[PDB]
Length: 9
Length: 273
Ligand SMILES: O=C1N=C(Nc2ccccc2)N=C1Cc1ccc2c(c1)OCO2
Picture 1 (cartoon, rainbow over the protein chains, first blue to last red):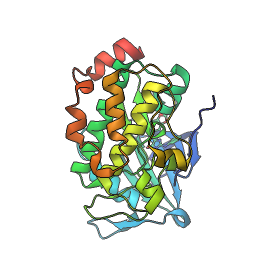
Picture 2 (cartoon, rainbow over the protein chains, first blue to last red):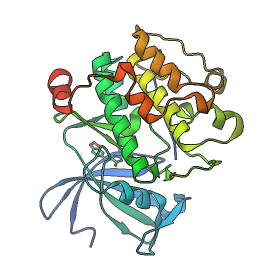
Picture 3 (cartoon, rainbow over the protein chains, first blue to last red):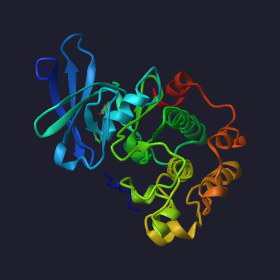
Picture 4 (cartoon, protein in one colour):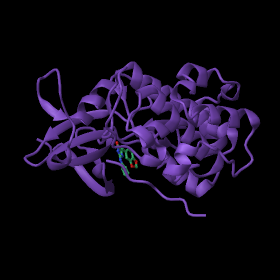
């Protein structure tokens, strides 16, 4: 299953 | 002068947080991280006791950078015509917690306890200092792999701590609480506790529990890995849909799952070395 980063700023 | 004081190395990363490079301070070869932020992207500005007008991030870092802690400290900063440059500590060897969990999968509870405990102490420190980070997540935690110490980074979405409502937010949505999703309103500590529940689930399950807004506001926590009943209880308490039903930092640290934490050094020897 896909794990990803999630942007902020 | 900025350019004669630091030797610049490779790019460590870039994104909403600017562009960050590895560097070494020429005076004593101390390892550093060098963060560049374009002025046009700084929406939130503060002022130092100096009276100097600076990005909020510089104000927050200076407030948390006194003494020792689990926050990556601001060593110095500079203003350029179109940008600010921040000189930050750089532990060596380091891996961020996002990459650590990707590579290692779901963490043994003893390791998650030690990490989570250190994050709690760091966040307490920020709050003691009048600082709310507002973007607590695995990506914003660095592990010093030799000392077994965790360090918070990237205060660019943060704020001065207050007791009244926040109606703005620039952090990571999948770590944001349901009252933000539903109402565009949150209170600082209670929103921090929710993001800590997301983080703890991330640690013991290997990924965050929610991706979609409807999952965030549903507050059904499905456990995809074997997690102890005591740990599930803590996570679910942190992820209470009503902010006033979430534990205080004190209640988190007094939780039975949190007792008998490893020291940083034991953590490195047992789990990291
Ligand atoms: O304050 C910071 N903000 C950072 N942001 C960042 C840097 C690279 C990718 C994503 C975010 N990095 C640091 C400091 C830092 C400190 C030690 C390091 C490091 C970065 O990269 C690897 O070792």
